[PDB]
Amino acid sequence: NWLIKWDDKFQNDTLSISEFKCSAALAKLGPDPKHPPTKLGEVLNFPHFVAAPEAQTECGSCWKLRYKGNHAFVTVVDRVEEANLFVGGTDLVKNLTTFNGAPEGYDWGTAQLFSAYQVDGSCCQQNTGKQCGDP
Image 1: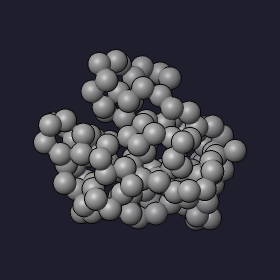
Image 2: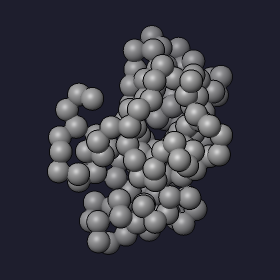
Image 3: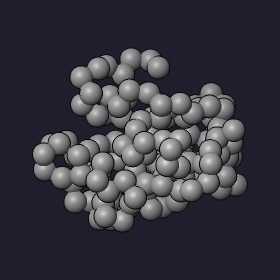
Image 4: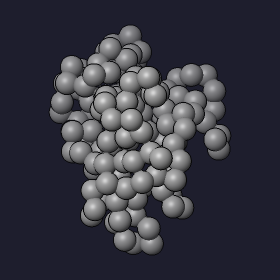
């Protein structure tokens, strides 16, 4: 029963990574794992980013989301404290939750997902060593 809502925060390239509750994990999620990104725009997989609840999702984890016949791979970069809720960047959500031209999720602002599950971080461009493939 995952929901997704959208918020411009998660595609705001200019925001300091300090503004996200996953800031420590974000520091390690630049294209150089030694030189922290300072801004959200520099983090791997930007802007397919979501806030998601602690315990259910780990900071920096990669999740495959499905809506109808669409899917996306998203990095958890912040927290919301509502169970089963993702809040994603506007364009991410708009694209995931458009069905045959109708931006269902975006226009309503909340959409229910068909499914969400964590996948290997390579799906979110992280250097795990593995190939994303087709999870």
